[PDB]
């Protein structure tokens, strides 16, 4: 799933 570490992944998607 989306990686919380990522800045864009968290900025657009929510942390797993």
Image (tube, rainbow, N blue to C red):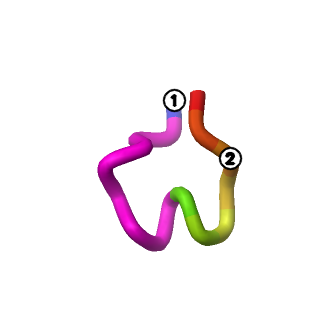
User: Which residue matches tag 1?
Assistant: 1
Q: Residue at x 59, y 39 (%)?
A: 15
Residue 3 falls left or right of residue 2: left
Mark earlier in primary sequence (1, 2): 1
Judging from the image, what secondary structure is the residue with disc 2 in?
loop
Mark 1 and mark 2: Cα distance apart in space? 10 Å
- The image shows residue 9, relative to residue 14, as above or below, that is below
Count of residue discs: 2
**Residue for point 67% across, 55% down:** 13
Residue 11 locus on image (x, y percent): 59, 70
List x then y, in percent, for residue 16.
58, 27
Would residue 8 be counted in the magenta stretch? yes
Residue 15, above or below 5: above
Give the crowd class for mark 2: few <14, some 14-19, many >=20 residues within 10 Å.
Answer: few
The residue labelled by disc 2 is 14
The image quadrant that residue 7 belongs to is: bottom left
Asked where in the image residue 6 lies, by quadrant, the reply is bottom left
Range of the magenta residues? Answer: 2-9
Q: Main secondary structure of the magenta part?
A: loop
The image shows residue 1, relative to residue 8, as above or below, that is: above
Q: Residues within 10 Å of mark 1 (few under 14, many from 20)?
A: few
The percent coordinates of residue 9 (x first, y second) are 50, 60
The disc at residue 15 is none
Relative to residue 11, is residue 8 drawn left or right?
left
Query: In the rendered structure, are the residues bearing label 1 and label 2 in contact, judged by CB atoms less than 8 Å apart?
Result: no
Rendered residue at 50%/40% (across/down):
2
Q: Secondary structure at mark 1?
A: loop
Foreground pick, 16 / 1: 16
Looking at the image, is mark 1 or mark 2 nearer the viewer? 2
């Amino acid at each position: 799933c989306c990686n919380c570490s990522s800045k864009w992944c968290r900025d657009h998607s929510r942390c797993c």
